[PDB]
Amino acid sequence: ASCTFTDAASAMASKTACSTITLNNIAVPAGTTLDLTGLTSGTRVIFEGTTTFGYQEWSGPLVSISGTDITVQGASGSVLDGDGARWWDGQGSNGGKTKPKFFYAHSLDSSSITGITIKNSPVQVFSIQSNNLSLTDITVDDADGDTQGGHNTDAFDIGSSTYITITNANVHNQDDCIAVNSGENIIFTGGTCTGGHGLSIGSVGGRSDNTVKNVTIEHSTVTNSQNGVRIKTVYGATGSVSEVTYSNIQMSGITNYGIVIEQDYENGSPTGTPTNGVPITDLTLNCVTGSVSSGATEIYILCGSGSCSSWTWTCVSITGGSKSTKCENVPSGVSC
């Protein structure tokens, strides 16, 4: 059954009786989720026109989709417009107004999301907690947040997930382009990230799931961002990061760290002293190149004692800025 909805209440009432769901120009009531969870396997969901959301201080999510064998599509020209400047106050999820997370993909398994454009998210965009989920041709347009107070506008937050593939993402935001807090068999490829805090593994630690294994971040560009490539493990936490590869990453206009791997991370500020409970092993950097700004540091490695080992770094060349004088516990075959 094919069904077209112009309001959220009708879509929610009938979602399980429809095998194709078209969501046309829906205005989602303030303080509520556009709740497309619990879909019948095989359902296709199409966003058309501009989806909007009422204003309320709450934690979200604004949209949530779940089910097995679900195909989610943005039609040509469609936008999910959060109008996040209504909430933005420079403090993100760290203070100020309570701001809603945008899009939950929790147990959207053996599924795909393609061609979705998100505009002006209040705070973080995708919360991915799924198995065998692809996200292709996603655009996050939070550029207005650069001047209007956007903060913590992460594009792809991943945890407790397996077999996630992100292809051809285009992100302009104010926080991580990708943040892998936990997960196994993750691929990010063909992406362009600008404005934000870079392509990050982590933070790893302090949650129920603190294991990252077999992640490839490749064939991507990071520009005008605080960091290019980053691995962050939480100060004093327990977990593990293994079999991570960054390959064919180009960067420019990086303001803090071209490459930063640190085991002293805290959300407010790193401690400056690393710990060794989240080992980073079998890390490969291959062809990670580009430039940082004049006030930036090229490469910063702050490893704990014994918690960084078996790294392979080839064709890493970061120009501009300054060399770090604060690296600790650098593994064999690696340098700052």
Image: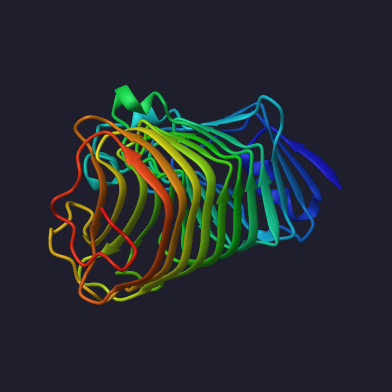
Whether residue 210 is visible here, answered yes or no, is no
For the point 51% across and 62% down, the residue is: 215
Whether residue 56 is visible here, answered yes or no, is yes
Relative vertical location of residue 232 with respect to residue 236 in this rendering, above or below: above
Residue 157 at what x, y percent from top left?
A: 45, 53
For the point 29% across and 64% down, the residue is: 233
Q: Which residue lies furthest to the right in this view?
A: 1
Count of numbered tags: 0
Q: In which quarter of the image is residue 68?
A: bottom right
For the point 62% across and 48% down, the residue is: 135
User: Is 297 left or right of 7, judged from the image as shown?
Assistant: left
Q: In which quarter of the image is residue 194?
A: top left
Q: Which of 158 and 274 is in front in this view?
A: 274
Residue 142 at what x, y percent from top left?
A: 43, 30
Relative vertical location of residue 146 with respect to residue 1 in this rendering, above or below: above
For the point 22% across and 29% down, the residue is: 294
Q: Which of 51 and 148 is in front in this view?
A: 148
Residue 134 at what x, y percent from top left?
A: 65, 53
Residue 11 at what x, y percent from top left?
A: 68, 44
